Every structure is written in structure tokens, then in C-alpha cells.
Image (tube, rainbow over all chains, first blue to last red; front, side):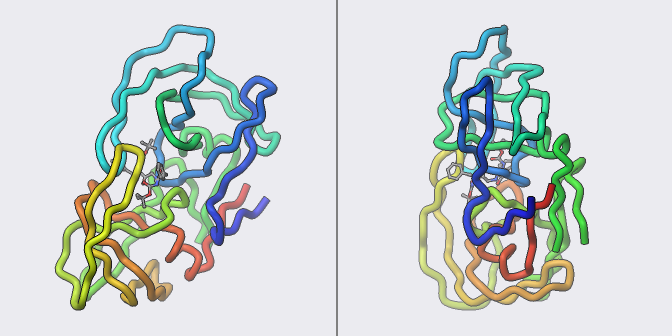
Length: 99
Length: 99
Ligand SMILES: CC(C)(C)OC(=O)N[C@@H](Cc1ccccc1)[C@H](O)CNC[C@@H](O)[C@H](Cc1ccccc1)NC(=O)OC(C)(C)C
């Protein structure tokens, strides 16, 4: 696909046969998902965004599917208002910015 | 051009006769820049990011060159760790997300 920016670039993700809405964010280095209980150990972490930091839990090697394109990597889970797919995952699906 | 995301999508912009580096951010609805004295009449505004709200000065109808492409629109000036080019200006330059 070719996603236009007239509207926020919100797509469907599948994180364990759960369809989830998430934003493709080129501005984000990391992937941040809404509070969820994932099996596995996590590492405490504080991530900064415009505005300040938020405390998140870090999970390694999560598999997510972005428009039926698989990506596997680190995800931070915390109280975000929106799921954010960051460049750590977008690089996996071959995502580019073209102008 | 075709920007890959192995690294942050940093481009050089020209604004108010100043060359600056800014991130192309499909996650941002608006363009927020580092503190600067741009010419004109501004209005205070508050905008939220993942860590909470910040106060910005809003400047309308400002000319900005992104990789030599012309864009004229709103620019928010405020306490940001990085200059960010949002979707109000990425659409003007014809940028897309592709995979
Ligand atoms: C998500 C996270 C991993 C925490 O990365 C950033 O927030 N990265 C910042 C850049 C940054 C680096 C270092 C320090 C501070 C900021 C990008 O603007 C992220 N794209 C912005 C996008 O996530 C956010 C989506 C959003 C919107 C509203 C609420 C919550 C979240 N929009 C965003 O902040 O938009 C404005 C900049 C216009 C405020």
C-alpha cells in the first residue's frame, strides 16, 4: 500500500488474533502500545515524548502483523492514548517516505 | 526522494532564512519547531503529545522549504527536543508512506 497523510495513518494490527488500530509513526523510534497483559518478563522503562516522560514496561520479541506483513521486536506498553508503530517495526515491513 | 527508516528521517529545512534539521513525522498532526523568532503575529496555543501538553506560539501562513519543496502553512514554535514536520506540511509536499 501507499498511505496518504490527509488523514492520520491508522492501520489494523493483529497482536495475537486481536485486531488493533495503530498509527504509523516515523517520528517514533520505538513502538508504544496501550496497556495490555502480555505473557513474559518485562523491563521497566521511561520514554519521553513531547510534553515529558511516561513509564512503560518493555517486552522483547513480540510479533505483530501490519497489514498482513510480520514484524518482530520490542514493544513498550503503557497508558498511551494510541498504539504507535515506530521505526523499529516499520523498517521490517519495508516502509519508506517518498516525496 | 525515498527515505528509508533505518535512521531517523531527518531533513534540512529552510525557515526565516535559517537552515535547520527537522524530522518528517507522520505521527504528528502539526509541525512544532524549536524556539525561534519568526516574523509576525502569533497566538498562544497548547498542544499535547504522549507526555502531556506544551504551550506554543502559533504562526500562520509561513513559508518553509523541505528538501527544496515549498510549503506554506501553520507552524507551532515551542519547547520541543527536535523540530518536527507534521502532516499539515507533509501533505503539501506530496509525501506518502509506502510498503
Ligand atoms: C512515541 C515515542 C516512542 C515516545 O516517541 C515520540 O514521542 N517521538 C517523537 C519525537 C521525540 C523524540 C524525543 C523526545 C521527544 C519527542 C515524535 O514526534 C513522535 N511522533 C508524534 C506522535 O507520536 C504523537 C502521537 C500522539 C498524538 C496525541 C497524543 C498522544 C500521541 N504526536 C505528537 O506528539 O504530535 C504533536 C508533536 C503535534 C504534539
